[PDB]
Amino acid sequence: EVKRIGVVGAGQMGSGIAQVAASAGYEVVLVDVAESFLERGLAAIRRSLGKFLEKGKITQEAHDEALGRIRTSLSLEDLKDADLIVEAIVEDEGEKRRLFERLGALAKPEAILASNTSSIPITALARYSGRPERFIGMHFFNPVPLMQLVEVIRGELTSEATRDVVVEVARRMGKTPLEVQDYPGFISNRLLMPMINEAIEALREGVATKEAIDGIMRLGMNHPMGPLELADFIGLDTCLAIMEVLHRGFGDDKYRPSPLLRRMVQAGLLGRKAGRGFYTYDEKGNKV
Amino acid sequence: EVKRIGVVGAGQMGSGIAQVAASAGYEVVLVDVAESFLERGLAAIRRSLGKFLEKGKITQEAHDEALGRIRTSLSLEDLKDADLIVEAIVEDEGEKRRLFERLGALAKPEAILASNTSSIPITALARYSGRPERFIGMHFFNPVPLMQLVEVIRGELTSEATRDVVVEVARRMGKTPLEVQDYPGFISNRLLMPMINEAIEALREGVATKEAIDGIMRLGMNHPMGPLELADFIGLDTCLAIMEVLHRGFGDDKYRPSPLLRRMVQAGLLGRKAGRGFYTYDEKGNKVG
Amino acid sequence: EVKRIGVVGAGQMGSGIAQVAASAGYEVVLVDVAESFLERGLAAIRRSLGKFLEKGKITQEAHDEALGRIRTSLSLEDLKDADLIVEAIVEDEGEKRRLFERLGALAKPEAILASNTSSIPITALARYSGRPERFIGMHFFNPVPLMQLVEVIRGELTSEATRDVVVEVARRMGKTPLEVQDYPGFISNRLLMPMINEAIEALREGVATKEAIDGIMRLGMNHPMGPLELADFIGLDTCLAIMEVLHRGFGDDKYRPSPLLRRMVQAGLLGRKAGRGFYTYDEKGNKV
Amino acid sequence: EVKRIGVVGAGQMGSGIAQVAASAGYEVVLVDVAESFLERGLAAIRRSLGKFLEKGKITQEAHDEALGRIRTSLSLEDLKDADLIVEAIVEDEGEKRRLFERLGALAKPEAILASNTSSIPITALARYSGRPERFIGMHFFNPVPLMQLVEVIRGELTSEATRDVVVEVARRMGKTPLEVQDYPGFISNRLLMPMINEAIEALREGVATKEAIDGIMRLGMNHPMGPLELADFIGLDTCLAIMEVLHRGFGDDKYRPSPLLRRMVQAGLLGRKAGRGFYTYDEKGNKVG
Amino acid sequence: EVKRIGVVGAGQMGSGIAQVAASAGYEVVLVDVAESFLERGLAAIRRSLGKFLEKGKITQEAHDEALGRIRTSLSLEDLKDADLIVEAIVEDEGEKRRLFERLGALAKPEAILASNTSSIPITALARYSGRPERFIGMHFFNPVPLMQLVEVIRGELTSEATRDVVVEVARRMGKTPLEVQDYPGFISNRLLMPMINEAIEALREGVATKEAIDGIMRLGMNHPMGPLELADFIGLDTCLAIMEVLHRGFGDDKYRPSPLLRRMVQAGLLGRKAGRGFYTYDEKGNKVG
Amino acid sequence: EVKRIGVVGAGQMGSGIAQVAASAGYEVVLVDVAESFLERGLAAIRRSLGKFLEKGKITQEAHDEALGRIRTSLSLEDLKDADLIVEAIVEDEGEKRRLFERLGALAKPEAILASNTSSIPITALARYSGRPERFIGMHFFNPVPLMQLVEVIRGELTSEATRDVVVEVARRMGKTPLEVQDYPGFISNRLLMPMINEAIEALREGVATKEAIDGIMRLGMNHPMGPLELADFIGLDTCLAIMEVLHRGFGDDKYRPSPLLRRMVQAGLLGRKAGRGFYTYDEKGNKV
Ligand SMILES: NC(=O)c1ccc[n+]([C@@H]2O[C@H](COP(=O)([O-])OP(=O)(O)OC[C@H]3O[C@@H](n4cnc5c(N)ncnc54)[C@H](O)[C@@H]3O)[C@@H](O)[C@H]2O)c1
Ligand SMILES: NC(=O)c1ccc[n+]([C@@H]2O[C@H](COP(=O)([O-])OP(=O)(O)OC[C@H]3O[C@@H](n4cnc5c(N)ncnc54)[C@H](O)[C@@H]3O)[C@@H](O)[C@H]2O)c1
Ligand SMILES: NC(=O)c1ccc[n+]([C@@H]2O[C@H](COP(=O)([O-])OP(=O)(O)OC[C@H]3O[C@@H](n4cnc5c(N)ncnc54)[C@H](O)[C@@H]3O)[C@@H](O)[C@H]2O)c1
Ligand SMILES: NC(=O)c1ccc[n+]([C@@H]2O[C@H](COP(=O)([O-])OP(=O)(O)OC[C@H]3O[C@@H](n4cnc5c(N)ncnc54)[C@H](O)[C@@H]3O)[C@@H](O)[C@H]2O)c1
Ligand SMILES: NC(=O)c1ccc[n+]([C@@H]2O[C@H](COP(=O)([O-])OP(=O)(O)OC[C@H]3O[C@@H](n4cnc5c(N)ncnc54)[C@H](O)[C@@H]3O)[C@@H](O)[C@H]2O)c1
Ligand SMILES: NC(=O)c1ccc[n+]([C@@H]2O[C@H](COP(=O)([O-])OP(=O)(O)OC[C@H]3O[C@@H](n4cnc5c(N)ncnc54)[C@H](O)[C@@H]3O)[C@@H](O)[C@H]2O)c1
């Protein structure tokens, strides 16, 4: 039944989702708002599939056939016969709302619509879609070709059938789909971001240096990255937005953002992407 | 310096601290309250040093010399000339208080006293010791011979000199000492335990199953253990006690224990050590069913 | 501006290109698909530099410093910061196309990409690269350490700046760069291969023996090798592929391969590398 | 006298023989029937010499010089001036016969011809060669670069001089040549294979499990591999073929193949190379329980 | 349930079985027919335990306690309350029969009787014992303190319970018990001895020298000893007796002893113990000439 | 303060000294006069570290890191920043003199120079170095990775500081440094070689056979090797050279070489390395 997958957004996540869908044997249409963004997206797909081929993880045939199953477009109308459309556009409720109203109008009636959103309520996006029973969260992990997890998020009205289809797509993509209810932060961000926020509060209070905090979590807890270097990697603007969703969604002070996180974002010290957050980065990323 | 190290408590942590001190070239006196506990402790040390020798991490000489530098005793008086005494007894403020009053009285004036406590304020233990400028937290990670971290916790009155001595001992033990202020949860537990507590709240609220929660944190965040299986490993009684220290010490509802964590502890479902917490364990401590 | 040169293919030509780049003072990253091929390539570089040292063409210092400037790698991503990348992989348009799509995606924007291709249109490879203004033919001659010529081939879109950079690299390598337009056979193969093909036709027609044909061209025209022994040296499969490129590219019967050349290739009589073409060879490649 | 060695067959054994000949300082011409087979052969030689280099058994120079002494060819005529030609082609008497008739015709008169055959009579191959006095068995052990033994097998007509030359080549290859007469199974297969066959019969009779049989021979007799896991390693088709040579060559029921060995081969349960014999193997050739 | 072990025969094997039983924590009564034999037996036990102590494989305490658990006796009646009695007397069916009839009469009803026999059918000895369900083969390997293997041999009537008890005793002795059915040669001798016999036949036929035969099996097959030097080590009289058991028990010419093996035994060339078999030995048992 | 160790001579001793320095955590530069000698040296280091790894005496990490700390070179100038340089070249005073004059000129002023010489006076080599207070004997035992002893030899002018640094390096190498004054034969050779020489004289005089002499010293005195088999192991040329240094240095006939030792050396019967001395050896160096 699922043969054709639409992906909206050829960014960090959408280009990975398009790749894993194509590698699984699905026909893929990847949509964005400018040719330059589509080109940047297929460049990321060629680099990733290229590494899989180089290290003997896939054959020449599978490499070339996967690329052959990806078509790019500037036109949402080219998703009219997709069985599943995965949205991976900017993390902005207004933008996703306008997209899902359009997708609800043009997608064939049996098409499932899915969001890769980190933080926006699945139930709200489901209402904007006009087909809430055929709406679900399909939350991938960065970078998509390397991360086995899909967090599958049921909206209030998500049907059993919708969940079964998306769980099977994840399995065909070589992923482990784990199901969660639509509450603020789902599981992934609800568990991760308050610990990062607590590290930032400990830093503000002078409990320890950034090096001591990151070293304690790496060496003591075997986290691959400490929370402050991880915040820099995610982006401090993204960290703040997720803490605000927890604070506003639970309505509980428990989830208040660190005032130092607010201050860093006001300063534009947004992490690796700005060349500076808690640490300073050179042009390649790497700390200095 | 420091030539002679006392370790009080030949348990899970103290037997590891004794081993790493001995392997570093320090003379060690390991003290407990019964011969059976000392025997269990040196059995753990022989098993660990045995594995290091077998895998070529140490020589026969270093293996034999390390064991040769460890003496056991039932008498605190045998610590009278220790340069550093590390306490690793039961996590109970009253017990540690009575021990530190005794150690303050009998240890030579220049001796530094240290606690491996997970949660009890270093500043309070420092006052009980009678020598707060020569008191410090020296917080090791389980299992001590394998975990490179020492969290070094300054009490209000801990001197620069005391910190310098203990940081150097940790380096000679092959550890990375990272310094933290004496506030509830230090860094390690303040960051870890509220995330475990949040996983337990998500489970109570029906947001996901225990398998989905642990799988998401393992696969998504590359945590070696998910928070619920980790809670079982630490002990749910220990998890609840640390959340209570954060709640009482910060005085902030932010750190309130999950009602499900309280209920599990009331039921005696304490994790691996009880054969059941979030998961069920066999006699070897592996999941079953 | 050019400090770092990538070479893809540690074969007959790529190992020579890597050597002359290293001897010229450039940092070299030499890439192939297996460690054994890289080892075989640096063994050829050590043998050649060893002969240059023995005959007093270079000093011990220059010998050791040249080897010191060559790193081998199985990862194309190690060419991310190369100023110039020269491709010397198998003569197959599909293989080169997939390589150049990958190189275009991973190389820094200012990097120039070049092909050592004998026959494949530079303008086509330039399109596959995604950066045609920064694409050029850089055609070396076998064996690269000994042959002074570089044939520099402008694609339709090759910039003046790209040509200037590659002409300067050739000069720093001690080579004479001579410029040609991207048309079938360039100059080198367009002039050489139809004369070899004509010798094969004269042989098929019974006009003379192979010895008479090669002797006439050696003694009469002062060619170092007659065309039939030269065909055996190049490989009859390579001769046929070049004649096919001339025939298909000009679309002109003038350039039709000799039916005897087709027949020899069907028989696997490919020349020196098969132990037999027009002549019979021993294991060392001498006539018997 | 021996400067130039021909090897026919760039397979498992021939590529090893070529390598050890080249490492010993001989010029080697390695012959096969297709370029792909020659490429596969020199790939195996580069991998092995690469490991010798990595472990400090040889220098970069000796590595490069050894490879420099190996030339490949599709033409038997290129063996016209070889002093010694060692055949390591398919174990098929007809194929070896056609090869040895050709080699006898083209090799210079003083050239010695040798077979690596496991089981075909040396005396018969010697007759096919047309120079039986200059024919001998030179039986190497898998893998050739690692195994010190050469079993040197005299045909009925093999001269003293032929034996002396081949014994000296084996010594220059760093091998221990041990001399045997041309009778079925020589020594190696005559002694080994009937014991493997007996283990298979004991298994068929229900005397013990495969694990008990292999464990008894490993622990009791200090054999590195038990006979059933060894049969799987050799290939049950090869084990059956060698038992048939003993049975037909001695003409004695003493050497009859186990009916269970026949049945396993009829089923295609050939051992490691088929993914299953007595034991089951994964793609890497390790057992799975 | 097994606390007390009887061993009958204080020879090469019985003194080893007594030692490993004592080292495992069992009370041991070691019986023979003369004081000199008992003295020779405990001398071998002191030498072996002495070497374990010197090399630090055991403590002084364990050394002294093991010797303390061994009593010697000339009276079978001293086995009246043994839980397990292991026979290790001369390899003679008549002698073992008379012993087992006596042991069946005097041993307490729940006592298990076991034979270390190399070759005599377990089922026959079981019948002589009068308690076949409580009879089993417990076949140790020379020298017992060093060899991990026990071959456990079920008689036709041996109970599951008897097998379970003897397998557990072997494990407490630090051994690996591997189970086999009572058929001629069990597994160990059925697999080993026909290959030794074949080496002797190849030698008689002039296929190769003794050095070539032993060298081929050492270097080619990674056997620690070649079959001819191994035959000398075992004793050629023992080799012939085991081949006779295979020949008579299977009733199959396949297992006929080599005529050269018979001739060597007729000449008294019995191997190391006679100073000459296939090889010549000095008084220390090293090859000479 | 000692971080970087130079070793000159990649022979039997120098390759062992380089290995033990690298295993102790020092950065090592190993120098010789030809590539083949450096290759033979690192082959011996790989074989030795390989055996330590195989028998579980070291970890994979320690094995790989030790090899990673060794660089080879044909240029003494690469020792310009060594803290300690240990010479282990040919036992020839003229060669060591020319080396130490060069090392004195190029090594940084605080660098200590040490000789592994068996027999040449430390005080003389110290004068050739131009920095006698920073010169010392550091005499290792064959084979270096297995032998715990370092004989530390004070020249007339060797400073306390120089001795302290070299004693500490020996301890970090896992060795037991024992201090001796610079007089002929130091302690090791002064005690050992006259007893070997006496065994040779007893053999020449027909007092006993070589087997009786070696058996008496093994069984009676618990020497692991008898003096004649030991002479074969050391090399009879080395034994003679050491006896000559005792004879010429003390100026005392007491230390005259056995005429049979001179005769054996004149015949080239040098011991294991020649396949024959007092005993005959196979290619593996076992008696025959
Ligand atoms: N980056 C992460 O690690 C990560 C992880 C999980 C989930 N997410 C979520 O995935 C989504 C995408 O994030 P990203 O990191 O890939 O962002 P990105 O900026 O890399 O990509 C966003 C893409 O969407 C395109 N786009 C914007 N508006 C559009 C519209 N109206 N129609 C079509 N295309 C439009 C942009 O041009 C761009 O190509 C967000 O909701 C984010 O919260 C991010
Ligand atoms: N984060 C954690 O996992 C955690 C939690 C709580 C406390 N701890 C800390 O770890 C250390 C001990 O924990 P463990 O897991 O090793 O425990 P354990 O119970 O295995 O060992 C403690 C040892 O102390 C001995 N002991 C008790 N009272 C004593 C006394 N008065 N004098 C001497 N010995 C005495 C006990 O007999 C026992 O051998 C303490 O410093 C404790 O504060 C660990
Ligand atoms: N050989 C000549 O005389 C000659 C003359 C001039 C031009 N050329 C051209 O140069 C090119 C190479 O020729 P050659 O003779 O060196 O061939 P070759 O077969 O010797 O070498 C090709 C190498 O490329 C490697 N390779 C293949 N695909 C690869 C990939 N994707 N990435 C990295 N390495 C890869 C192969 O493993 C091999 O080592 C061809 O385009 C040929 O037409 C050849
Ligand atoms: N593999 C072993 O363990 C082993 C042990 C000892 C002896 N042997 C014997 O060595 C010989 C080779 O065995 P292998 O395992 O190397 O086999 P293999 O199949 O790996 O190699 C045989 C090679 O011979 C080539 N070949 C076949 N017919 C040929 C012909 N007529 N002329 C030229 N080349 C020809 C094939 O192309 C192949 O490359 C056999 O006689 C075998 O019995 C094998
Ligand atoms: N020697 C081996 O390698 C070996 C291997 C395994 C099994 N076995 C078997 O073990 C048994 C013992 O062999 P061994 O090598 O110890 O022999 P042994 O001759 O060394 O010991 C036999 C002992 O039994 C005693 N003995 C004889 N008759 C007796 C009797 N009626 N009552 C009590 N004691 C008596 C003898 O006095 C002697 O002390 C034999 O059945 C033999 O086949 C021996
Ligand atoms: N071999 C022993 O058992 C032993 C014992 C202790 C001391 N020593 C002493 O150690 C020194 C080394 O002896 P060895 O056995 O290692 O000798 P070796 O011949 O094995 O090694 C000497 C190395 O020095 C190199 N060399 C020669 N001149 C050189 C120069 N000018 N610069 C750099 N390298 C140069 C040679 O090429 C060779 O690789 C001698 O002084 C010897 O007396 C030897």
Image: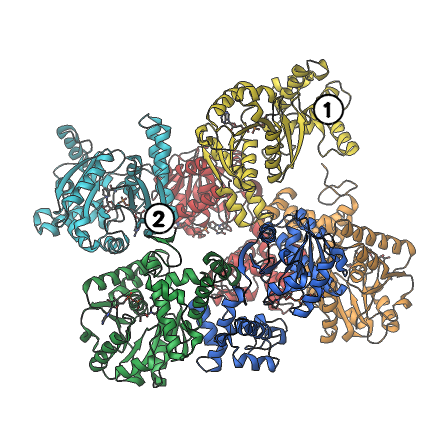
Chain colours: A green, B blue, C cyan, D red, E orange, F yellow
Query: Dot 2: few (<14), some (14–19), or many (≥20) neighbours within 10 Å?
Result: some
B53 left or right of A36 in image: right
E252 left or right of D110 in image: right
Helix, strand or loop for disc 2: loop
- Where residue E89 sits in the image (x, y, percent)? 83, 60
Asked if the beta carbon under badge 2 is closer than 8 A to the nearest atom of ligand 4, the reply is yes
Q: How many marks?
A: 2
- Where residue C209 sits in the image (x, y, percent)? 17, 36
Q: Amino acid at mark 1?
A: Met
* Closer-to-camera residue (A259/E37): A259
Quarter of the picture holding the N terminus of chain E:
bottom right
Instruction: Indicate the chain on which mark 1 is placed.
Output: F
In this rendering, does residue C232 appear at all?
Answer: yes
- Residue lying at 13% horizontally and 42% vertically, measured from the top left: C180
Marks 2 and 1: in contact by CB < 8 Å?
A: no
Looking at the image, residue C208 lies above or below residue A81: above
Instruction: Indicate the chain on which mark 2 is placed.
Output: D
E113 left or right of B238 in image: right
- Residue A145 in which image quadrant: bottom left
Residue F195: numbered disc: 1
Cα gap from disc 1 to disc 2, whole angstroms: 66 Å
Front disc: 1 or 2: 1
* Closer-to-camera residue (F16/A211): A211
Q: Amino acid at mark 2?
A: Val
Q: On the image, numbered disc 2 is attached to which residue?
A: D33
